[PDB]
Amino acid sequence: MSGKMTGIVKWFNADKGFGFITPDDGSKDVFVHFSAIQNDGYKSLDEGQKVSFTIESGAKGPAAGNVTSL
């Protein structure tokens, strides 16, 4: 089961729809794909922006889900 957490968008390459978010807890970077973006408009993230999402630690590491602006 994933847990809820906020963080700041570290880098998001719209060209691939892939990016990483740095949790406010200072934990390891969480992988976020455009598919996780529940925000209106084009699915993407703006570096420096605070966001909120759930974190599920898989074999490939922590993955973000249900991502929306904080």
Image (cartoon, grey):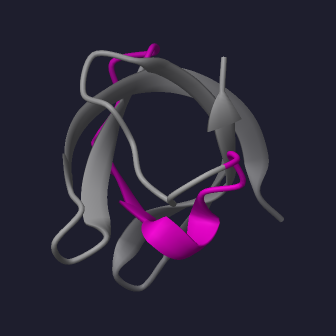
Start and end of the magenta stretch? Answer: 24-40
Q: Residue 38: horizontal and vertical position, in percent? A: 72, 54
In this rendered view, identify the residue nearer to me: 38 or 66: 38
13 inside magenta stretch: no
Quarter of the image for residue 8 reads top left
Could you say where residue 65 lies in the image, as x and y percent from the top left?
Answer: 66, 60
- Where the N terminus falls, by quadrant? bottom right
The answer to which image quadrant residue 61 occupies is: bottom left
Asked if residue 24 is positioned above or below residue 53 in the image, the reply reads above
- Give residue 67's position: percent from left, percent from top: 65, 47
| Residue at horizontal 26 percent and vertical 56 percent from the top | 19
Q: Residue at x 76, y 45 (%)?
A: 3
Position of residue 60 relative to residue 62, above or below, is below
Q: Quadrant of the C terminus?
A: top right
Residue 53 seen anywhere in this rendered image of the structure: no
Seen as rendered, the residue at the extreme right is 1
Check residue 35 for magenta coloring: yes
- Nearest the viewer among 41 and 31 is 41
- Residue 29, given in percent of the width and then of the height, sits at 28, 43
Image quadrant assignment for residue 53: top right
Judge left or right: residue 35 versus residue 34: right
Residue closest to the eye, 7 or 69: 69
Q: Can you see residue 40?
A: yes
**x 45%, y 15%: residue:** 25
